[PDB]
Image: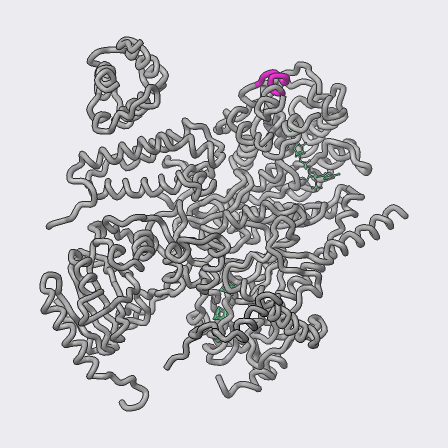
Amino acid sequence: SRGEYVVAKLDDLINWARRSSLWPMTFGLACCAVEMMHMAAPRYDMDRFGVVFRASPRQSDVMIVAGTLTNKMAPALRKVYDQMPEPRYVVSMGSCANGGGYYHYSYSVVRGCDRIVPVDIYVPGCPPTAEALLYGILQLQKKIKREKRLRIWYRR
Amino acid sequence: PLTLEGIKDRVLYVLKLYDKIDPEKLSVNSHFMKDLGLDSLDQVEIIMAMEDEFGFEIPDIDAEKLMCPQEIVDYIADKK
Amino acid sequence: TRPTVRPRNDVAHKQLSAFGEYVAEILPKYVQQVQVSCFSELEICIHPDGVIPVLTFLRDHSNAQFKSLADLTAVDIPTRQNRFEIVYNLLSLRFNSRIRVKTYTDELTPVESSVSVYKAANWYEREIWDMFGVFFANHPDLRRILTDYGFEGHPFRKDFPLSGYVELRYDDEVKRVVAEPVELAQEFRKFDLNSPWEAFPAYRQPPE
Amino acid sequence: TSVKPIFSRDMNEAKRRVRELYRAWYREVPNTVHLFQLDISVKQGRDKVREMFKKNAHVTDPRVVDLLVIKGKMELEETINVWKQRTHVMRFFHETEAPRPKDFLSKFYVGHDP
Amino acid sequence: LVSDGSSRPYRCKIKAPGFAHLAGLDKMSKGHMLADVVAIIGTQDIVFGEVDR
Amino acid sequence: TYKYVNLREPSMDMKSVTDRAAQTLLWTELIRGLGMTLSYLFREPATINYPFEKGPLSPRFRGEHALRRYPSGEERCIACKLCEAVCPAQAITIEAEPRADGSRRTTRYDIDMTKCIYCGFCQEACPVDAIVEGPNFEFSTETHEELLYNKEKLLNNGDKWEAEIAANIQADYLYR
Amino acid sequence: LHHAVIPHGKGGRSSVSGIVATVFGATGFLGRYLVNHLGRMGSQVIVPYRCEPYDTMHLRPMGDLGQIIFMDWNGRDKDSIRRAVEHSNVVINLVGREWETKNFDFEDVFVKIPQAIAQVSKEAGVEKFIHISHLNADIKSSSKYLRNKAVGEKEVRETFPEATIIKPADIFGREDRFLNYFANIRSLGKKTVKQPVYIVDVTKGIINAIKDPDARGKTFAFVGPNRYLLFDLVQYVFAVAHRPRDKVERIHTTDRTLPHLPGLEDLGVQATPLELKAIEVLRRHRT
Ligand SMILES: NC(=O)C1=CN([C@@H]2O[C@H](COP(=O)(O)OP(=O)(O)OC[C@H]3O[C@@H](n4cnc5c(N)ncnc54)[C@H](OP(=O)(O)O)[C@@H]3O)[C@@H](O)[C@H]2O)C=CC1
Ligand code: SF4
Ligand code: SF4
Ligand code: SF4
């Protein structure tokens, strides 16, 4: 099946192209923002993995929900999420974001962020030490490596 | 063309335009608070609806003290 | 006693005692209590009428400067007919001393809007209006700070429970975020930790 | 037993302020449905406004009526500006049922609420 | 701190310098433009974990 | 004692004012800033090659939430609920039953890794040191179900290694 | 029945309701809204999917913490589908594409798919199997789609006889095919009688029929209140949008009534007409 061979190789090529750079947007409310800045630090690079910190939600590949999400914040967070280009992926960073965390039993704190957006990679820690976030971004890249998108477009 | 019965007729059909009144039932001493079964809520709705229709502000103590459509016409002839 | 215990300085104790006795004897119109703690920080307990004269007297008069204003919190106490407590905190730049102006207040009758004499109390009054319900009379702008807009209930009260009455979630039916009545994921066990046997004999209040 | 009132002496000024606030909310709604781009006609919004006014229609303490005037005026300010977004104005409505009825029988099949 | 005689604090409260600094934003930016407003937000170290209490 | 900045005056000697005007017209200290930045250009970069060179750590890192057990023995825990009492997030959830051996034991021991703020209070509160903040911090969880650990996930997490945790505790049983 | 299957307390968001529902399809439109109403009800929904997990990722978090479950299936193996519906209370068949693929015609999807899954569900022993069809899908001509839906109705009524056959009219919502198709056109003008019905009334009818008892066997048909000309509807679409072969034959066939079998009045829900919800959904015109 030379057509299936071509579709498999071309899907491998375009999924490599997708997982190559993956420039995020740094949403970053509380101290998890400081830790995102500290994995933007000179010791732990991001440019080695093609990752560039960038304040442009009009072109951002993945979105890193980090910090304590509140009721006064969450419509603005999803309104940022909605003006995002449709191939989109979500990293929930931090105990506050991945299930409520320390301010769980509390008004004006959304219990997690599944109540707002879907989540692809949970990375726990408080703050998740930058090596753990970087391993989470590697597992996100390998999630992009396992997609079989064009194969499903073939055999659909 | 500042005719008093023209004011009467235009008040009558904007009360017709108000849909929560049954019937229209134009009178000189109608008293649509208690003789027609309405709240002061609908009273102030009708008063500032007349304000919406043809002009001046018609303040709130006067809205407390109109109570009757012919007296609204006489109040407009007093004020306008 | 001599190690492991913070000593107290009776010089400052006598000085703050004499100063509080001075202030209490020269403003008889609004003073009820001047209490001195063991650690020598003054507390002045005040009827809710002379807020503006006591603050204008305590900003000036050159026997006590106290130009610096800090926090205001009205900590909510039931089993009092007048519940809430306005706690002004005043700091002198020249003297290095701290006086806690506690005036009492109820649920509804306003205290007299200290923003006119201390400009640092603007967001303090707005914030304590949002969180408690202590109204301030003839204040410029009263809005909601540190809550959601559509939220109400004055949540730092004791009648408002720990978990709120709302719970947001996104849904795709109406394509937006909506609020439902609260559904916990765990009970929040409020443990019983009040142990008996009277650890402090010096604070035994006289019973009935 | 001396209490400083907020705004009013007797219920007359209380009624005057609350009907003034209702007049403002009546002339404030179509601006909101034109600005926030809501999804509900003018009649239904005005009916739930008059419903929320008719809900607390039996309170006679003038301090409490003045304080509800202050509450409604704060919400009228924050809705006549563009601060409160689409979520809060839809949150005033209840279209996300919760169809929980007030029978005895349907309250009996879904129990523990007498 | 406000402490009833117990093992629990009855009521804490926090006076925040970021809140006190941000209170005077009008009297810092009465006569400038928006880039200078970003400079004013810079020159007082806001973090808003603390400015919120 | 104080040391305040910016109290001078620009000089009236012609040499000083023409040096300042030369700085103004001639972009001088801008070029000196370029020289400083090129002096940091020619350093060697202090980046660690991440998946091959992992970062430095401590003997007492607070990680993985792995239980321990006795030397050639059974489970170390008791279900004495001290960790659940001290847990500030209240993420610990314990249900105890005793078994046929007579000694007291458990049934259910759940840690909400979502809620866990990673303090060390349950490490320092266990009287037998059963629950230990583990060594490594590599969780990276796709679903939301998998961040809710059972007793068996904790025991497999503590039987995939103890010699690491034993080495850490044998390193620093003297401070805590 | 075992415990933790009965309902508990209030409704939804970890308030455990009664049903355990396995939904086939559930990647597109109506399955998405039905999964949303079952997550509002607070049940456990087994959704299997054959496509890429990005789509079920975008419709993922509508259920609560780990309530809904994702699994895998195909249109070829009975054993994977039997593995999917091993343990379930109810199962709904919502599958079907409105064009032929390279690998599947309208043949064997409406033909092979409900026979196989209804066979293995009857071999599993579940209740209240609810199968969708379209309104007025008879044996007669002009549509392979409609005649294969007639064959599928005959299949689901033939085997597993206590299956709830359900059929709506042309249904519109936020991601409709025909109403957005009328929006995204260019043109021609003809006559046809037709009724639409807004999607939340249909799916509230489905959830009330699936949790209210003893309504099995009796096939249902959902009736909109308006029931007027297609050409007036298309002029209404151009008016609200401010701008003055298989699918076009399937919309120019007809829509006639079958009034013998009931609708929403034996179920107790408001049917919302076109005006309100159509002004709601018709955004995205000029400016
Ligand atoms: N006018 C209307 O819209 C009406 C529609 N209906 C019915 O409602 C249902 C949903 O409508 P619609 O908007 O079109 O949503 P879909 O067409 O997306 O729903 C069909 C489902 O079947 C899946 N599917 C597609 N091809 C195959 C295949 N070859 N084998 C197995 N599964 C397949 C789809 O994608 P995936 O594989 O990703 O799961 C999807 O989950 C349809 O079954 C339709 O017949 C009924 C009456 C009126
Ligand atoms: S998870 Fe921890 S580090 Fe992150 S925002 Fe919350 S408190 Fe800060
Ligand atoms: S403190 Fe230690 S022994 Fe006690 S319940 Fe917790 S892990 Fe078990
Ligand atoms: S580290 Fe803290 S939050 Fe985590 S389980 Fe231990 S005591 Fe609880």
Q: Position of residue C8 (x, y in %)?
A: 24, 83
Q: Residue at x 25, y 78 (%)?
A: C39
- Does residue B36 appear anywhere in the picture? no
Q: Up-down: is C103 above or below C19?
A: above
Could you tell me which residue is drawn at 45 percent across and 62 percent down? E46
Quadrant of the image occupied by residue G252: top right
Residue numbers of the magenta segment? G227-234
Q: Residue at x 11, y 65 (%)?
A: C27
Q: Quadrant of the N terminus of chain E?
A: bottom left
Among the 4 quarters of the image, the one containing residue D72: top left
Could you tell me what secondary structure mostly forms the magenta stretch? Answer: helix
Task: Residue at the far front: name it.
Answer: F14
Residue A136 at x, y = what percent?
A: 64, 63
- Quarter in which the C terminus of chain E is drawn: bottom left
Residue nearer the viewer, D24 or C152 = D24
Classify residue C123 as left or right of residue G264: left
| Magenta highlight on residue A130 | no
Question: Percent from the top left, x then y, of residue B28?
Answer: 21, 11
- Quadrant housing residue F168: bottom right
The residue most toward the bottom is C2
Relative vertical location of residue C14 with respect to residue C84 in this rendering, above or below? below
Q: Please count the marks in the image.
A: 0
